Length: 139
Image (cartoon, helix red, strand yellow):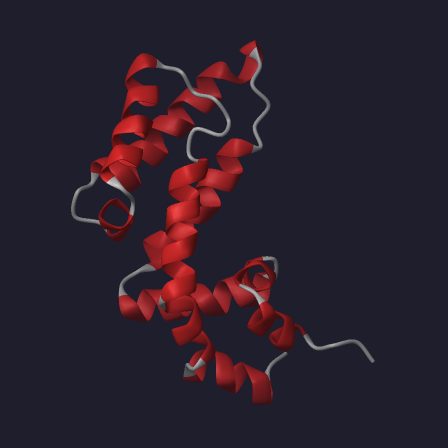
């Protein structure tokens, strides 16, 4: 009998985010707190970084980088913009403006947001009813 998933989610944020049920439960908790943008931004960067830089998907990667910049960086109100360093935001903005869209261009912002999650919402999620009750009666 294998170690149940909820125990791996308590090992690391990475294990939690590798599991469809854990992603859904973590995102629920963030929605209750008004921080779901942290998790969506985090997944958006991964989605972007895996696209192969080639001339055939250069429009695709460009609108995608623009969409991530527009939704999570440009928006000075949102939680992602307030939790990433100003120099990191200007750097990303530079890449967008000059159209230098290298696959790792969001990686440091993603690292800052990941740190934000491991410092507050991820430990809080592990003390939450959403998680603890999935532990008793989950499917």
